[PDB]
Length: 126
Length: 186
Ligand SMILES: [Zn+2]
Image (spheres, each protein chain N blue to C red):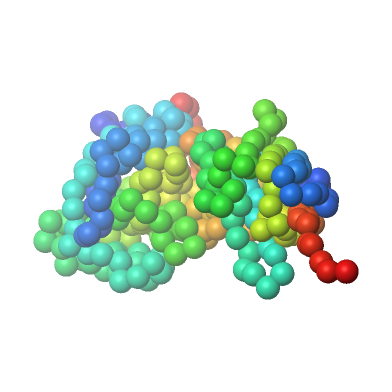
């Protein structure tokens, strides 16, 4: 009952910034938690940041105070401002929406993923 | 028609054994539930709910919500505090949710003012403040309301935070199960 589409990924250098955007269409009031997850090669998918329908936010410890989540007035667009980026932030980033049925519980909706690559310098021999 | 006096119907809300409930949170659920029904078809003429907040020794065996309600309704049948009140409405209440964040459960279309019996009109509800209206939604189901296409209705299948019945079909069903007839007006 909702559809998600996110954008804004790219390759940046260490210390750089990126701004991700996710647009939801459909039954917007069904979105109980609107958020961002990421998955890096070989690792499990993990929460980055989310926001509840009442405006309460959560951040992963490793991105708190470098990343900021926000939601526009219309409630359809979710932003992730990513500052001071590190190689450990390289991952596919997914927009996510949780809906909750009164008797059925949680259901997950996902975007398609946007690739984020954070390069740092690899010194090598000659 | 309009009865000679409103029927006293108890809504007996039993804190699950081992749970910790907070006063403002449970009060919000019970007042939202009462108001969701009184707002329909002038129903205060037909029913005055006594919401009773008490305790039970019962606890759900796990986070399995269907198992939990089946056990709760059974526990009422030999609960000496409920003896003589098998025709009332019962909720098991806790702070948290059930498995996969199920918010509540109910036996559908289980209360009618004329046939209520055997503790059939029972359900369960979270009381966390972030889920307003769950008890009201489950009480709707108990009174025969079905899920609606309108996502701004209390009885949308998905939790939205809304608190009021909007479906004419559901309002007619709920009010009929409490003694109302169309000729009575609002
Ligand atoms: Zn329902």
